[PDB]
Amino acid sequence: GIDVVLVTGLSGAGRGTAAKVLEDLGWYVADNLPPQLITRMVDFGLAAGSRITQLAVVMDVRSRGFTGDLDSVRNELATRAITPRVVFMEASDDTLVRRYEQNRRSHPLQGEQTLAEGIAAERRMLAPVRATADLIIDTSTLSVGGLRDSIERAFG
Amino acid sequence: GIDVVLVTGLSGAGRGTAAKVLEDLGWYVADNLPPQLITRMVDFGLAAGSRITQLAVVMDVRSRGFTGDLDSVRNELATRAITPRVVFMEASDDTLVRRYEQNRRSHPLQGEQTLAEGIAAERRMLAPVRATADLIIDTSTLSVGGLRDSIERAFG
């Protein structure tokens, strides 16, 4: 069949290094893949007569097309005699901040990706609260003063 | 009774300015308050014979002690004849990044709070995945090379 490893974790905790180690060990690594492509890729490879028997996926969880859990992926893989192995990368807040600050110097596009992942997680976490808000104030493009003006106007 | 306003939103979208505007309009503002304190505060104020009839709360959402929704708070306040008004602050990613970069210069402790809010949201969003992981790799304190060594060891 196919061995499947799924890599995820916190920004800066080492998902990129885990993918590099797996590639070095002979895995085919699909990076930034939202979960839907896993089954389609496995089904494709099975039909494709692929030499690839070891698939690792670095999961794109910062996408609206991803529920909170992996029970959907596990059950669909189960119907094809595959039990994925899930690897989760984490670290203390102090370590993650130190790595972000180093990324600002050495890998600025990685640093910007880290901010983008944090904001995407906030938006997903706050979505039920947003959906019940009585007033939403969008402060895009506003200066410090324009921010104050817009809120004063919104509150009457 | 008491008028209750609940303020939340994305890091850098203007929750602090909203709280300041409400304070200026006469509200008593409880900042960084997780939801549980709201009704205890209302019940206390009601029992205390408070002059405070206008309570605004900037909600502490980056807490393990906070489910995803506000339906628990609304129902509990409903049994006290109070309908809260929920204000949600948001902005584009480009605006939020620009404000974070300005905070790094002008309000560095607010910049650190923004990173801490992003990491807390990631941890909350990834909690179901973490709870199903086969392997958790904690990379706290590790150098770039030590990160690589720890993952190589974890993978065999």
Image: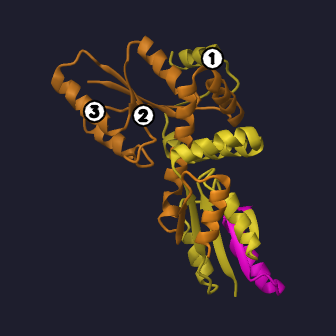
Chain colours: A orange, B yellow
For residue B46: magenta?
yes
Q: Is residue B105 above or below residue B83?
A: above
Callout 2: helix, strand or loop? strand
Q: Is residue B10 above or below residue A42?
A: below
Q: Is residue A122 above or below residue A112?
A: below
Residue A49: where, in percent of width, then height?
Answer: 17, 19
Identify which residue, B76 or B91, lies in the foreground. B91
Dot 1 crowding, Cα within 10 Å, few <14, some 14–19, many 20+? few
Residue A65 visible (yes or no) = yes
User: Which numbered disc flags the more N-terminal residue, 3 or 2?
Assistant: 2
| Quadrant of the rendered image containing residue B24 | bottom right
| Quadrant of the rendered image containing residue A111 | top right
Amino acid type of the residue that numbered disc 2 sits on in the rendered structure:
Met
Q: Which residue is mark 2?
A: A59
Which quarter shows the C terminus of chain A? Answer: bottom right
Residue drawn 67% across and 64% down?
Answer: B18
Residue drawn 55% across and 51% down?
Answer: A141
Residue B60 visible (yes or no) = no
Amino acid type of the residue that numbered disc 1 sits on in the rendered structure:
Val
Residue drawn 37% across and 37% down?
Answer: A34
Pointer 3 and pointer 1 on the same chain: no
Q: Which residue is mark 3?
A: A81
Callout 3: helix, strand or loop? loop
Of badges 3 and 2, nearer the viewer stands: 2
Chain of the residue under label 3: A
Please provide the residue range marked out in magenta: B32-60
Residue B11: where, in percent of width, then height?
Answer: 62, 50
Dot 3 crowding, Cα within 10 Å, few <14, some 14–19, many 20+? few
Q: Which residue is mark 1?
A: B144
Per the model, the C-alpha gap separating discs 3 and 1 is: 37 Å
Per the model, the C-alpha gap separating discs 1 and 2 is: 22 Å
